[PDB]
Image (cartoon, rainbow, N blue to C red):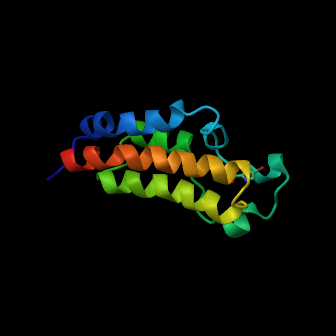
Amino acid sequence: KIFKPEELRQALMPTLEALYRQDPESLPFRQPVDPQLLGIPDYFDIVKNPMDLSTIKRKLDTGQYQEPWQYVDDVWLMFNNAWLYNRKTSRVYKFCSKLAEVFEQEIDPVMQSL
Ligand SMILES: CNC(=O)c1cc(Br)c[nH]1
């Protein structure tokens, strides 16, 4: 089974759009964390592989995922980064947990279809 880049994009894009639709919960995740701008120099000492929704979308728009599990890996990487860096009751952590719930509720039938 080989995937065509625009077909893979059409199949997965609704799952990414569902994350983007969440307001306010997608807001911390719509752009890359910039530790200098945010004044959190420790960020890249804990998060070695940053990921965010804008980067996932760009990868999905430019054929960077050959297989659907590569996309699923990047979504979970974004989540796991936030769950490692932030306090459990912080806004970012709580918002992350909402996005992961949305992602769970949705990604199963899409993967079954691929
Ligand atoms: C995904 N964003 C974060 O994990 C983050 C930004 C700031 Br400021 C603290 N945590």
**Looking at the picture, how far across and down is residue 2, in whole percent?**
17, 50
Give the percent coordinates (x, y) of residue 33. Answer: 69, 49
The answer to whether any part of residue 13 appears in the image is yes
In the image: residue 71, left or right of residue 23: left
Residue visible at 65% across and 34% down?
24
Give the farthest residue toward the right.
Answer: 39
Q: Nearer the viewer, residue 50 or 112?
A: 112
Q: Residue at x 48, y 57 (%)?
A: 76
Q: Quadrant of residue 25?
A: top right
User: Residue 1: percent from the left, percent from the top?
Assistant: 14, 53
Q: Residue at x 28, y 37 (%)?
A: 11
Q: Can you tell which quarter of the image residue 79 is in? A: bottom right
Would residue 114 be visible to someone looking at this image?
A: no
Of all residues shown, which one is farthest toward the bottom?
Answer: 45
State left or right for residue 66 relative to residue 3: right
55 and 77: which is toward the camera: 77
Say how many tags the image has.
Answer: 0
Q: Residue at x 22, y 41 (%)?
A: 4
Question: x%, y% of residue 50?
Answer: 60, 56
Task: Give the residue at the far left of this rendering.
Answer: 1
In the picture provided, is 8 more to the left or to the right than 56?
Answer: left
Instruction: Say if 93 sits above or below 4 in the image.
Output: below
